[PDB]
Image (cartoon, coloured by chain):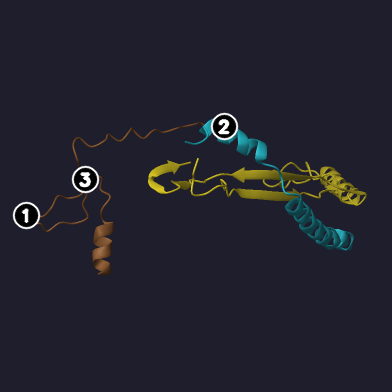
Chain colours: A cyan, B brown, C yellow
Amino acid sequence: TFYSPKEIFNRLKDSLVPDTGLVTQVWADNNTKRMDFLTAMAEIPQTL
Amino acid sequence: RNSIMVTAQARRDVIGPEWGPDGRFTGYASVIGTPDPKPADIVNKFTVE
Amino acid sequence: WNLDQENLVSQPRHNVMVKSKLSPENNIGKTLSVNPFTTAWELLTLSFVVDWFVNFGDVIAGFTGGYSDDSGATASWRFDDKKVFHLKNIPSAMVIV
């Protein structure tokens, strides 16, 4: 005997939740990348 | 001897291959009367809409 | 339930992604156009050429002031788990989830 598939789906759907550590890490990575991009584009005035 | 182990472990075929014509049996189980029926194995399905 | 495994284990592929755009405040519109003459220079004009170039110069002047944009992020999961369980002491019993 076992659970029903629909009950299992409900359990899983309630169980899913974003990971704080992963989200924080990706924010840090995108932050580093965006710092690099912004610093890189700081010299467009020199181009003009 | 371990080969015979595996052969005897090749049993559990509810009703194994019968005793050999010269008694040369294999992984085999002998039934007494009408064997007990095995109930139908069921499937439980759900669809992710 | 006498399942050989006493805890259902599910391994999802969990996605975490963030992407930003970071565009400035400028006039990237009409200025990005093909030659106003291209093949229509035969319309004799120099004042119109001056207008095109002064518009271009003004646009290229008015870009430095502003620079900012937004970002997006996605949280995802995908399940592909098909598990098996022995009935304890009864391997004949097969349970597929």
Q: Subunit of mark 2?
A: A
Q: Are marks 1 and 2 on the same chain?
A: no
Q: Subunit of mark 1?
A: B
Q: Secondary structure at mark 2?
A: helix
Front residue of C91 and C19: C91
The residue carrying pointer 2 sits among few (fewer than 14), some (14 to 19) or many (20 or more) residues within 10 Å by Cα, namely few
Cα distance between the residues tagged 3 and 2:
38 Å
Q: Subunit of mark 3?
A: B
Q: Secondary structure at mark 1?
A: loop
**Residue type at the position of mark 1:** Pro
User: Could you say where residue C80 lies in the image, as x and y percent from the top left?
Assistant: 52, 46
What's the mark number on residue B15? 3
Q: Earlier in the sequence, mark 1 or mark 3?
A: 3
In this view, the residue farthest toward the bottom is: B1
The label nearer to you, 1 versus 2, is 1
Front residue of A45 and B14: B14
Q: Quadrant of residue C37?
A: top right
**Residue type at the position of mark 3:** Ile
What's the mark number on residue A7? 2
Q: Left or right of A44: which side holds B22?
A: left
Q: Left or right of C29: which side holds A14?
A: left
**Residue type at the position of mark 2:** Glu
In this view, the residue farthest toward the right is: C65
